[PDB]
Image (cartoon, helix red, strand yellow):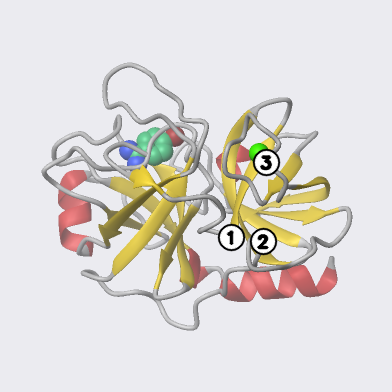
Amino acid sequence: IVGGYTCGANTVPYQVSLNSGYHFCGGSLINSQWVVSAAHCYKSGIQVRLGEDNINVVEGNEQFISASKSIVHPSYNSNTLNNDIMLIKLKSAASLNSRVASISLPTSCASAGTQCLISGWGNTKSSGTSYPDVLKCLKAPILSDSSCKSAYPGQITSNMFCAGYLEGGKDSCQGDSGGPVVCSGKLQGIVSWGSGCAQKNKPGVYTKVCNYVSWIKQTIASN
Ligand SMILES: N=C(N)c1ccc(Br)cc1
Ligand SMILES: [Ca+2]
C-alpha cells in the first residue's frame, strides 16, 4: 500500500497473509474454513496466517493453518487477469474472535463513489521497494466504469473495477495482491493488478466480488 496509514494491530480482522516460507499475498477470511484471494496468488504449499499485524514477529493473536485445497476460478485467464479469484479451504476451522473474524460477501455490487478500505503488507513505494512488517490501510473510492476504461483502454472487463485516485500517490501494490477491498462492511474487491503503483491516471484494478457470490457459495457448499 502506497500512501496509506498503519491500520493498527487486528483492526482488519478478516485480513490474512498467505505464507509459503514468506508472505506473498493477502486474502480475506469469509467463514471459519475458507479464504478468498486472487487467482494470480495460486501456488501449492500455502499456510494461511490469520490474526497478523507484524508478519515478522509472533505477537500472540496469530492462527497458522495449512490450506487443504485451493480452487482457482474455472475461467481465470492469467494473460488478461479476468476472473482473478481463488478459494482456499483451511485444514481446520479458525477460532473466530474480535481479532480474527470473517467478512461478509456482498448482496449488491458497490457503486462508483463508494469509499472502501484496502489493506495489505505490500510495497509502500511507487519507485523502489520498501516492505512494511505491519498491516497498511488505504481509504479509496470506487471509480466510475468510464474513468476505469479510459485509464486502461481495452483491458477492463465487467469482472473488474477501479478504485483509488487518478492523481496518483495512493494505491495498492505488489504484495497486496489477493487482499480485500471492503465497502460498507462487505467484501467488494480483491487486489488484482495495475500499471506500476500509485501512478497518475493508473488506479488499482480489483476483481469485482459481487459477480462471484453464487460461485463462491456453491463451491463452499460442495467442498
Ligand atoms: N494497485 C496496483 N497498482 C497494483 C496492484 C497489484 C499489483 Br501485483 C500491482 C499493482
Ligand atoms: Ca505476527
Residue beneath the point at 53% across and 44% down:
77
Relative to 123, is 47 on the left or the right? Answer: right
Amino acid type, mark 3:
Glu
Residue 13 shows which numbered tag? 1
Residue furthest left in the image: 167
**In the image, residue 69 lies at what x, y percent?**
82, 50
In what quadrant of the picture does the C terminus appear?
A: bottom right
Residue 59 shows which numbered tag? 3
In whole angstroms, how far apart are the C-alphas of marks 3 and 2? 14 Å
Mark found first going from the N terminus, 3 or 1: 1
Q: Nearer the viewer, residue 58 or 151?
A: 58
Secondary structure under the numbered disc 3 in the rendered image: loop
Whether residue 73 can be seen here: no
Above or below, 84 against 124 in this view is: below
Mark 3 close to ligand 2, CB under 8 Å: yes
In whole angstroms, how far apart are the C-alphas of marks 3 and 1? 14 Å
Mark found first going from the N terminus, 3 or 2: 3
Residue beneath the point at 59% across and 50% down:
27
Q: Which label lies toward us, 3 or 2? A: 3
User: Disc 1, disc 2: CB below 8 Å?
Assistant: yes
Residue denoted by label 2: 100
Q: Residues within 10 Å of mark 3 (few under 14, many from 20)?
A: few
Above or below, 164 against 111 in this view is: above
Amino acid type, mark 2:
Val
Mark found first going from the N terminus, 1 or 2: 1
Amino acid type, mark 1:
Pro
Above or below, 222 against 15 in this view is: below
Relative to 113, is 8 on the left or the right? Answer: right
Residue beneath the point at 21% across and 69% down:
113
